[PDB]
Image (cartoon, grey):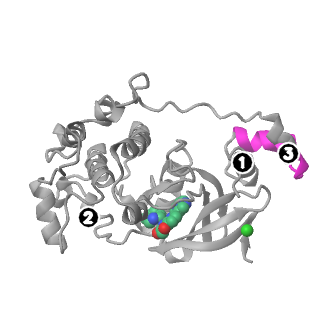
Amino acid sequence: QPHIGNYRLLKTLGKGNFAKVKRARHILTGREVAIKIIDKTQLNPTSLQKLFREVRIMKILNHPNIIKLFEVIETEKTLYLIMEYASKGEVYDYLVEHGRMKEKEARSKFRQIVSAVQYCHQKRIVHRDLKAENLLLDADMNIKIADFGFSNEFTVGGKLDTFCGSPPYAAPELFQGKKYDGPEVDVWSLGVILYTLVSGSLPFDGQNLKELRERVLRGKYRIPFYMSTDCENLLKRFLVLNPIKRGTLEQIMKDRWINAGHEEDELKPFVEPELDISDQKRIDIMVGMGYSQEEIQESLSKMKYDEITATYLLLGRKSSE
Ligand SMILES: O=C1COc2ccc(-c3cnc4ccccn34)nc2N1C[C@H]1CCCCCN1
Ligand SMILES: [Cl-]
């Protein structure tokens, strides 16, 4: 069975553009991972430098509902990004199989989604292509957002991608030729996401791009009879045609619907904790693998994304049968 570094490569999860993503297993710890594989020989110098800038963004996104990077392996021809594996797959497929979520379930996921996106907006990182296909689910049904920081050509793509993203989630200012790079475009996409979680369907659709474009620009969508008033009111804060009249995520975190059942636990911007790099239990395990204590401290304190960092972080995740 093919390997790369400390990883046994397993089945392909997806493939498209310049990327493939495979399930794999870290041999030293037994932990499952996902590996994004990019054939560098397909890239020109400009696109190669763009890819490396986007990897450097991935390196600093550390949120429980954002797919985490564990290791970078680079050969002359190929870049490998070893990432968290979300074992329950795409929200897209989950909604197709099971239908709409009850509002209690949708709220749990949406609090995670909003926290993850607001955290990246703090660092002035805009996703620009949030969609059901890159909202993933871990073994406990927690959200893990994929491809935050990456341009479309370095993702395997979703089914309907056109103009570098999924058209049903594209903000109206993109169809009018307007600026397309600030947090407001993600806020629109989040409104489309909330609607799809609670209804099982998209608010704006069409048989072709021209029809969908006109539906998005008109901004009108159906409110299902079963949707609560508070959910409808929350959607009104995302799905606003004029971008500067949209809520910011920090304001939306105070919304009644998003905090229902969380009256003593109001949603607030994520505060990243400092990484404990001194866990002697894991350090002793790694010494047993032949790593030295001094090289563990060097790799973790400089956050190198080498085989030592990956092993330490993976030992901090629960195993799975
Ligand atoms: O296309 C499929 C088919 O179904 C899947 C099932 C599981 C995973 C998966 C699990 N854990 C991770 C970590 C990173 C990336 C993907 N995954 N992916 C997939 N995708 C890839 C996924 C990547 C984001 C861009 C749009 C397409 N979705
Ligand atoms: Cl295996």
Quarter of the picture for ligand 2? bottom right
Callout 1 secondary element: helix
Disc 3 residue type (three-letter): Ile
Q: What percent of the width, then of the height, locates residue 168?
A: 25, 62
Region in magenta = 287-301
- Marks 2/3 in contact by CB < 8 Å: the verdict is no
In screen coordinates, is 126 left or right of 246?
A: right
Q: Quickly name the residue at label 2.
A: 167
Q: Which mark is residue 285?
A: 3
In contact (CB < 8 Å): disc 3 and disc 1: no
The answer for how far apart the CA atoms under marks 3 and 1 are is 13 Å
Q: Residue at x 87, y 52 (%)?
A: 289
Q: Residue furthest top?
A: 264
Identity of the residue drawn at 71% across and 53% down: 306
Q: Which quadrant does the N terminus fall into?
A: bottom right
**Residue 180 percent coordinates (x, y):** 25, 53
Measured along the vertical axis of the image, is residue 121 above or below residue 8? above
- Mark in the foreground, 2 or 1: 2
**C-alpha distance separating marks 2 and 3:** 48 Å
Residue type, mark 1 in image: Thr
Which tag, 2 or 1, sits closer to the chain's start? 2
Hey, which quadrant is residue 129 in on the image? bottom left
What's the residue at 22%, 52% (across, down)? 179
Mark 2 vs 3, N-terminal side: 2
